[PDB]
Amino acid sequence: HHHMLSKQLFLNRCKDVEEYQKAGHNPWPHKFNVSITVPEFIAKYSGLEKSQVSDDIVSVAGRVLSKRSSSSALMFIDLHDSQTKLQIMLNKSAYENKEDFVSLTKMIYRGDICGFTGHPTRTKTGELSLIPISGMILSPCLHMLPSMHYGLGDQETRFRKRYLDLIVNPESVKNFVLRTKVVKAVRKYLDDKGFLEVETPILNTIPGGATARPFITHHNQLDIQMYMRIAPELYLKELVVGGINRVYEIGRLFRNEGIDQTHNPEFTTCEFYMAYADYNDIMKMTEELLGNMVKDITGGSTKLEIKDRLMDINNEEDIKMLEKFFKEPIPRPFNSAECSKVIEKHCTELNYYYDGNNEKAMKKLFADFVTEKKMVLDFTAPFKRISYVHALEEKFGEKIPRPLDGPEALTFLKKQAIRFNAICAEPQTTARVMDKLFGDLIEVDLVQPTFVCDQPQLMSPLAKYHRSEPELTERFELFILKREIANAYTELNNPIVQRSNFEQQAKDKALVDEVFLDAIEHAFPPTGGWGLGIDRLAMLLADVDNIKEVILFPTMRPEDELEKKAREAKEDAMVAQEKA
Amino acid sequence: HHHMLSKQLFLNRCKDVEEYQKAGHNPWPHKFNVSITVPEFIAKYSGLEKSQVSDDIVSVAGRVLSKRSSSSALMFIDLHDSQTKLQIMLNKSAYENKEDFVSLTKMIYRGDICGFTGHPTRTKTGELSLIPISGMILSPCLHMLPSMHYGLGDQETRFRKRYLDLIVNPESVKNFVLRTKVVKAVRKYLDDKGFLEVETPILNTIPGGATARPFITHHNQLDIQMYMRIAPELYLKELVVGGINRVYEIGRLFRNEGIDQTHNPEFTTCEFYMAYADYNDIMKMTEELLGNMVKDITGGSTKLEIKDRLMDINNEEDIKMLEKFFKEPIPRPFNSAECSKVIEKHCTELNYYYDGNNEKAMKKLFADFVTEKKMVLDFTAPFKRISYVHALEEKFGEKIPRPLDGPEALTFLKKQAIRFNAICAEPQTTARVMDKLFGDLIEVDLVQPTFVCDQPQLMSPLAKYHRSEPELTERFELFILKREIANAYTELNNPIVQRSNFEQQAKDKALVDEVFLDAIEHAFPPTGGWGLGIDRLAMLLADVDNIKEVILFPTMRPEDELEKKAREAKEDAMVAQEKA
């Protein structure tokens, strides 16, 4: 009988609560008057010396995570509030209602939400505490909370129940705080420049010309099929046509696709559009904004981070890797290395063959780095800037044949497709081969914040041509840690050309958004467009490997009961753990 | 051949643009340097006296809405920017490139986006203007803009194309500004009290126990059916269980139901939850917050509004109604009244029979009021407060039989169901009869902001019992203009009772959210819960009759071509209007 002990505990616990209620104690009182929060408490009363007790009577409340007694008249509780600890020293002599003191000191279970009213102090042991005159159960806990910490990594157990994870892994809260620090920073920056935050439809009657597979739904009264938005771009642009020069939306976007650790079915991005601005303006704006952000997380525009790349030469890095390997090991070519590495890798459910240095580097990245190697991302202005094609050309050795979409230029390009990367794919259209030639080539290293600008019209189907040098467009993509964080355009405002683009896109896909085309046919001002993924930026700044760390409730494949029975089984493996 | 003239115009206009480009003029330049906005312009240079010209050279840009010439060397343009007008006085003598002066002065079509660089001035006629040294087309308009104003009411033409409506009805922009003023006010109020703004899933794998019909969608990789959220309540509460004491979300909610002028398929609400608070705390918070809002729209906590109720006794109101009736008319009993009223009502596509005083009152409400009767909503603290049942009892004459869900109390209630309202419905369950007895009874008048508190447990399935007086719950509903604007609870935190409620709800409906139940089983702190509809509050504060006035792109039944051909037909009825 699996889950026997947990069931037993839950039932007995319910009994506890109803006997507590039977004795004239409300386990769920309506209002408890918290006079001060635990951080405020610490800020105010940390000046108290040892054995000193304040005359102030204050009242606090939080979750009990520890309950230890050195005596029947002296109990020590770790109360937690806003991810901050404060000891409650229950002394019977300093408690008014002695009867209630006994009933309460017995009733308190680990996990309970309690409130206490009494005097601040700092004990002889140095621990800042409160000596309660009174106190009560605000809400009883009916299950055994997992010990702290719990589930690291094991992302499944963590993100199945966020409400537990937040408690047993309070550090995680920081992430989400950071996340909002981001959006505030955005709002403050844009609102102060006269931007109007707006809301555009998530449900659309048109699928659109985008490739990405949308979620499909259906409205009944209208009896029409609707599609969840891929991007708010066109609506916002229609607002700019409407006469609202500066707009932005920090909205939820949806994609009916795959779920990686860098992809969630629904995610948050910000887009803004600004009349009479160009991508240069947006470049400075991006510099400024991100500067403000990382300064708001620190105080300076540089930010310390984890260096996950290991150097088989840096003996410090090697020493760190050995220290984190829960032992110590070394070799030269293989043999011993192979055995120890395969042992640890099999122990951590990792993979696979070779047992070589590559696996060592990977392990060092995904595990060791927290203990060791740091790095610094410099968000100081100005950011490094490069043109798309002259990075490629600088490095090739010389120019690319012009008419870049022509045969001669292509035939040029695969020469270095074979010479440099030794990687491509087919169909080798000019676009693809060029593109990540560029990306297993120059896209790394792009660790520091870097604008890659002036992409070819080959790469830019819906952009506006560059105002000077030919075959290029007025764009940029912001790269940090070898990834695209944000992007901007000197938006295309030619209605004729844009109609061509749209109607071509439609056929390449096989209706075209005629509404938008009408809108820009009514004259669309010169506009700067900007886009940023909030989730991914948050990932970067909180320094986390998984997108589930910055999304409170990521989309989970619901539990089929092999998962259920497994988990429940191991939780009673927990209670049997406590006893024997 | 319908739409002949519009097609002709569009084509000829495209010709105009390509001949302009052929002559060496870019109709869509990349970047124009706007040094100052039109409001900033007016703020800075309004001090200029008549015939006076500043030495300052500034550059501005916006949409041309008027193009008049008194001469071939003197032209007057109304440039519009941020819904603000500024005259451009093109004088050939004060323009450098004369060639460009002629080409440009001819090329400019009404609707174009133009930029000008020159000297501020105020003319002899008193009109603040700019005398351009140079200037250019930033983006040409390819259709004939409707005259200002256009489409009032005729909500279809308006809200089909928001980008046109914003231009020809710029006043509407105010609404949306107001709307954001609301949300900022919320954020500022909550963030300053240590609230963490968060984002919860819009896509859920569980339908829930709510009655409202959800949008249904499907994720492919997981191959599971998902449901759009009705409310974020449970997620947020799980966050409070998690240890984040104060959370809120200003999110998009979805309902797969009907589309009234007070209902949109997707709408925005704010919900917050605050540990160790009760509904009283929330009452004061609501007072404070809304006070701040209406003060931010005005400067004082009272707000002037339209009184749409007509008094067949107030001769001023009658005079107003006659003035707005595009003529003047009166009578006594009927006859003349019947004829004139039926004439005007048929003329405005209104309905229906009787031709009595009721129809007159209705018309006065929906049309006349803008010109006349005002009113003042007082958002000054404190708001009026009433208990649910003792309003009813005060007015009945005496108490209601207790055990209110019992037979005797019910049999009491329908006595006044027949005596007062002369309206009910069946099945006359205790709930329904009581409920809007109350609502065609005391729910009006509730014009001033008023908390209706302490609803019965009959009315409150998922609320927490009142801490003192029996059979009541700790709730409130905020009523303004006879409608529910916001609501709050001393949230139910009893896991046992809540499980009972949920599992009962499920059966009444015919899966139950077991996750949430687990969460609160792990002890849910005493919490205050609060909810507010942003769209509806915006409706109230902007003083508008339709929800489409506060939603940029409301959900529209796509055009079948009877609508299309009709509209296009009447737009060439427009161009034929200009000529003959």
Image: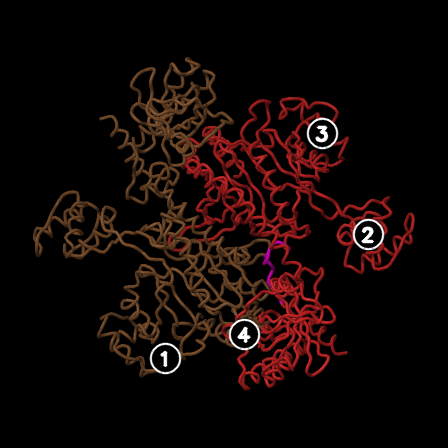
Chain colours: A red, B brown
Image position of B404 with respect to B87: above or below: below
Mark seen at residue B405: 1
**A567 within the magenta span:** no
Kindly report the distance in space between the C-alpha atoms of the residues bearing marks 3 and 1.
Answer: 82 Å
In the picture, the disc for residue A353 is: 2
Which chain does the numbered disc 1 sit on?
B
- Please state which of the two labelled residues, at mark 3 or mark 1, is closer to the viewer: 1
Task: Identify the secondary structure beneath mark 2.
Answer: loop
**Residue under disc 3 on the same chain as residue under disc 2:** yes
- Which residue in the structure is indicated by mark 4? B495
**What's under tag 2, amino acid-wise?**
Tyr
Q: Which residue is mark 3?
A: A414
Q: Main secondary structure of the magenta part?
A: loop
The chain under label 3 reads A
Q: Considering depth in this image, is A293 or A270 the residue closer to the camera?
A: A293
Amino acid tagged 3: Lys
Please indicate whether residue B172 sits to the left or right of residue A230 in the image: left
Q: Residues within 10 Å of mark 4 (few under 14, many from 20)?
A: many
Which SS class for mark 4? helix
* A383 with respect to A422 (left or right): left
Foreground mark, 2 or 1?
1
